[PDB]
Length: 134
Image (tube, rainbow, N blue to C red; front, side):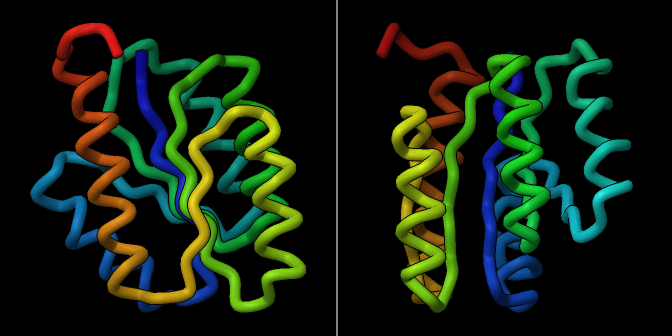
C-alpha cells in the first residue's frame, strides 16, 4: 500500500495553494518539472517499501504519462486531478487515463481544484486508516 495523489495543474499558483491544503492532511507534495527528477524520485516510490502518503504534482503532462505507467507496474492507488485551459488537451488526455479506470477529474477553477483534492485526500485517507471494505 501507498497512495499517490496525482495532480497536473497549468498554474504554479495552484501548486503552492495545494501544498497548504494538504499540509494539515499529511500528504507529502512532490513537484516534478524535469525528466531526471521524475526518474530519480519515482524509483524511490518503488524502492521505499514504506506505506507512505504521497501527493505528486507534475505540471508536465509528458512526465505525468511516464509517472502513471511506472505506477501501473507497481499497482499504487492514484486519484488524478487534471487542470488544463484547452479542453482539446484536457478531455483527450483525461479519457486515455479514465479508460484505465483511474479516478480522473477536470477543473478550470483554482478554488474548486483545491476542493477536489480534499475529496481525494479523505477517500485515500479511508484506505490509509483502514475503514470497512469499499
